[PDB]
Length: 177
Length: 180
Ligand SMILES: [Cl-]
Figure 1: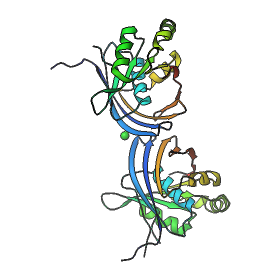
Figure 2 (figure 1 turned 90 degrees about the vertical axis):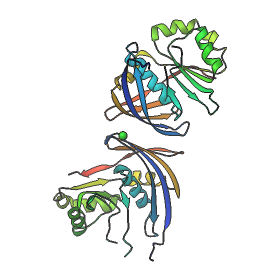
Figure 3 (figure 1 turned 90 degrees about the horizontal axis):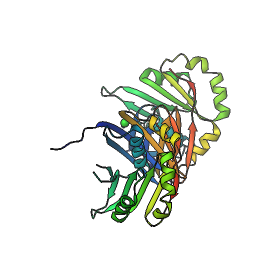
Figure 4 (figure 1 turned 60 degrees about the vertical axis):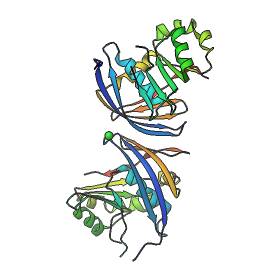
């Protein structure tokens, strides 16, 4: 049947979330379409690491970047990227117990946040994280066709590591429930 | 038959080794004889983490003789011999001649400085010997993780070991006195 034209990336990841006491090994598969920049892909991956779960899956139209479904087939977590509009955010928030949004394009995001902050506050179950240009570029450097990563999370800070390098990642919390 | 009088410790351990590109889960079991200090047992556990392998087994001679842990190959030979303490020439010789690779974990500041001063030039003669030291301070902090039932996470990068459980998180820096 149908298939996506895309580049396949594999990541063996170890996550130690010391805030949550969440310890997990997973092997992730990311499909990157020519329309997706390296950064946005790595932001996806970062997103996954922050909400690491055995059940948390990527997916692709109008679906989230990733979702975690429960035993009754409903959406526990909806992960979204970019700078969505009123109708898009409403779609996610009313369809999912929790929504986590990752905003990223500095110039674009500030204008979007100035024009939306007051409207996003309307959704009781919405989290908004921002990651600035520099950090996004640094996260993106970790990109490899085959990746082996370990992520330690403590006090909101994400310590991201491979064989060669070590990076402190600090997501900014624009909104929290 | 025969059996050791000892206290049993269980450890679920997850190791994320970035130096060796190896992620591993294991259920360890340590038997601690009354003669063994808590520190020495925790040093064993740490050494297991550094050389983590599905086949790396602790062992003690019931009949002393044996290493603290060894890793046997498919032809029943010893690939890795892990030794703890401050052994003499004959003991070291026995380990290095019987094993492809020997890892010795020295500890106790006072005794070890003397030992290394009178042995540096003699260990160097064994081309398959690695000597790691852990200082008194670090050892005590590693010792603090001891519980009869343990859940441990370890990340390794640049020879540094980030060790953690549900309470605490600790950076461990073994000193390399000698490498092959
Ligand atoms: Cl692996």
